[PDB]
Image (cartoon, rainbow over all chains, first blue to last red; front, side, top):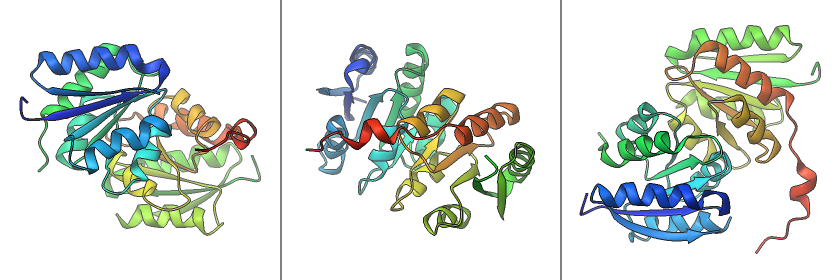
Length: 125
Length: 134
């Protein structure tokens, strides 16, 4: 986890939850790359990953749907939109996801945190 | 509603859900196209990109791998939804023309109410139309 560089970006509404998630990531040993607060925060999160500067990016959005669509439309990005820990577990084990979209308007913080936690610790098969 | 052509495709494990959602859409007046049981995603999406269906519904394990692959196709916007609100926003804000559902993660009644909200919500093209890119 001390090895893994984890990038985060959010829209305006998602800043609070993003920072909460960053702090849970730091507290479990992850290296946090806070990419800031807004399209804009789209290319930005995904480019940290594709250019090798970050191992994955965590994108915090309204529902996550618009961002998951956009993220996946980029070369070398596999973006999972998860609403349970099982989703995040599968996203990694089966889909080698390198981006997690989370919906701040749709997912409680503690649930977003347990989804994040599982995404970060699951290895690809 | 009577005017809308909806395509349906699913993986092996997703046939029960697919059929069930097909029945539900038929009875609410939709024109259903059962395309059958990641070949099935390319197939679902191609009904949309060729002009044969208005949207496609894709029943998967989690929906995650299908939504990724579906979104890699030009002119496809695939929404993996787990609530009716997700479905509503996927259409209103994102103009999704593909819905991904996870048969392993979503219960049949929740999947049907997601579908029903997906099929009856229109894109808000107007507000997005004049936004200035760059």
